[PDB]
Length: 242
Length: 232
Ligand SMILES: */C(=C/C(=O)N(C)C)CNCCOc1ccc(/C(=C(/CC(F)(F)F)c2ccccc2)c2ccc3n[nH]c(F)c3c2)cn1
Ligand SMILES: */C(=C\C(=O)N(C)C)CNCCOc1ccc(/C(=C(/CC(F)(F)F)c2ccccc2)c2ccc3n[nH]c(F)c3c2)cn1
Image (cartoon, rainbow over all chains, first blue to last red):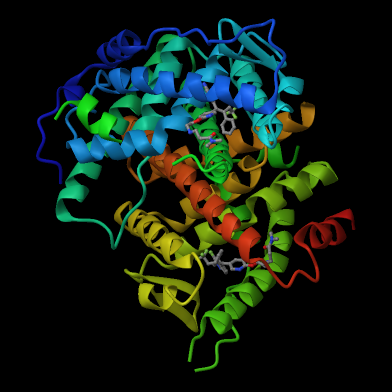
């Protein structure tokens, strides 16, 4: 199906890992004043500000993910529109691994469960994120594995379409699936290099990709809450630079 | 411990043996929004009874705590209905085989509230399974994975659940190796299938939002039915 000659598809596993590690966005500081007690609007202010800012840098990151700028502009936009909260979340749970009971939103913004209660609904999402981070800590998730998963989330985010598909959209989806197969290869390689048996490799690949269902769930629940606070892309198009 | 000893071939055998009966709708051969929702609700409610009986036969599930058995089914039931739907629908491009006498096209999908958006997503997933030539043996592995995964993070009890999930991954790989796939092709197909499950979860979440909205005729809430059938 795909007609595109994409550099990503002929990268070796090591080269894919290197490119992903190089793409990582900068580490950002919240505008959080620790002498200021939290209220609902103040916490939602802090988080929203952090999310808006992370989104700018996420655009720059996505441009450096091999295979991503080979998609049509419309398809790049769609992936980012679908995936942004999942991508924030996986970042959060990775950073929070060595902080049992707490979510490291930023270096200066470390929140425990109880501080989630200052916003209606949000402690439910907090618990799920905490559980996810503990899961990654127990599995001893490696940085190289993390960046593979975050790229998988981006590429897998798009809405499934049958009646709503065009011949062109279908070529684009085929290109996505090839990029995804390269990332799977890269994950397996990393595992094989770390000394896992073949059985252990296939088991861990499954365990990590099953956690992505949980990330999707958390994002969906997040989105429901944001939509019900009346939140409501010309950036995206123009930053993605076409 | 019997469950944890199963070979790949034995796992397949047990899961195939656990499969529920295929149900018929009460459909009488015109569809309103109200009669369609009525038909779908009555079907879902009858499927649920058989889903509970099925889950009791998935290796390892009756080793779990009552809480875990109830919680896994409460979180997963719509995903489980949906995977079964898209599987049954693979030989019916553009349609959804809710039951043998209830085969619906997207036109009929517009009958009911926020089914229309979900409908195309289900058709696409069916189409993806068809294109991948998903086999029945792979389908029952994936459906048991949904059960054991959908509530597992939402400590030694979580370990048992994880060990059984690993066994099913081993079973999938075995099936693929037996079908002639290379090791590379095995790991790629595994990943492709598990990423589809993210999308099934998303479809279920979207469906749940409409069920909460709408809402119901909730005489026997699912949590009560689960407790009755599993406390027992
Ligand atoms: C009462 C409210 C609650 O459910 N609640 C949690 C407060 C209604 N309870 C009975 C369950 O009702 C029910 C379940 C499933 C479906 C259903 C569909 C069809 C589709 F969208 F998934 F395609 C549905 C329609 C509209 C909104 C949500 C879901 C359905 C029914 C039967 C199925 N068999 N295989 C499947 F995949 C099915 C899906 C409707 N109502
Ligand atoms: C909507 C307008 C509005 O609030 N009103 C009142 C009109 C704002 N729309 C922009 C997006 O805002 C966001 C995005 C993300 C979040 C994050 C959270 C935290 C958690 F729940 F995910 F934990 C959130 C809170 C409440 C509901 C949904 C999400 C968030 C922020 C920063 C992050 N960095 N890494 C992450 F994982 C997150 C998550 C808040 N507001």
